[PDB]
Image (tube, rainbow, N blue to C red):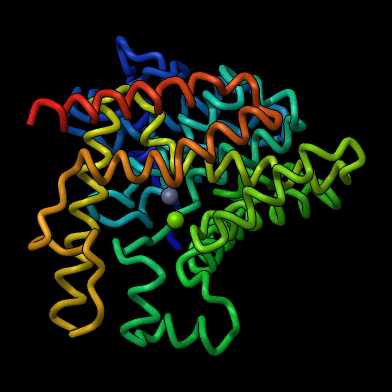
Length: 333
Ligand SMILES: [Mg+2]
Ligand SMILES: [Zn+2]
C-alpha cells in the first residue's frame, strides 16, 4: 500500500467545516457532503476533527500526520456504493463520538478503549462491495468458499479486519504505533473483536451477552469493557433510525438502493432474492423503517439504555419520534 502524499493531506487540511458542530447529536453529514464539491475531503476532515477533538491520539503517541495518513488509507479502501462507502464509516465514527461524550459512555471505558472505538469505526467496513455475507455464500463466490472452508461465515467482517491489519502494519499510518506490550495487543484485539461483532447474524447473542454482563456486578471487568465496546460499535452501525427524521430517511434510501443492486445481481445469477432486495416488490420505505424499528432498533436501544447506558436515552426518544413520523406517512397516504 502506497504512502499518503503531502498534497492528499493538504486537501483535507484546507476544509474548515464552517457552521458544523461535528460533536452534536443533530450533526447532518448529508448537509456537510452538499456543502462543497469535495465531499470525500470534508468527510475525512470530519473524522480528523472528531479524533483530534477527543484529545486521544495525542495521549497515545499518535501524531496529527499519522492520524491523517490512517484516515486517508481507510478512505482509499471504500468503494463508490450507495450505503457502505466512506460516508457510512465517518457517520459511525461521529455517532460513536456522541454515544461516548454526549451519552457519557466514555465513563464505562478507558481512554485507550475510547480511542480504539473511534479508530475502529473508520475500518469496520473496509472494501465493502455493497453485497452482504449471504450473497457470497449463496453464489459460492471464492470469498464465500474460503469463509466456508476456513470455518468462519462472517465473510465480510474477517475481510475488513485483514485490510485494517494491512493499514496498521506501516508506521506512517499506524495510530497504535505509540503503544507496546499489553496495550498494543488490547488495541488490536478489541478493534478486531468489535469488527467481528458487527455481523448481524450474531446480533441476538452479542446483545444477550452484554445484558447478562451489565446485570452481573461480579462480571469480569475486562470482559464487560470488551462487550461494551462491541455493543457501542453495533449501536453506531444501526444508529440511522436514532437520527433526525430527514437524515434517517436519506440513509434508508441509500440502504434500499444498495439492497436493490444486490437483488438485481442475485436475479442475473439465478439465486434466492429476498423481498427487501427486489425492486419489483416496491416495498414502502415507511413499513420497512417501522419494521426495523419494532423488531431490531427499538428493543436494542431500549435494552442497552435500561441495562447500563442511561445517558443514551435520547436514542430511544428519537426512535419513538421517527416511528410516529413514519406512522403519519402511512396515515396520510
Ligand atoms: Mg459491516
Ligand atoms: Zn457498517
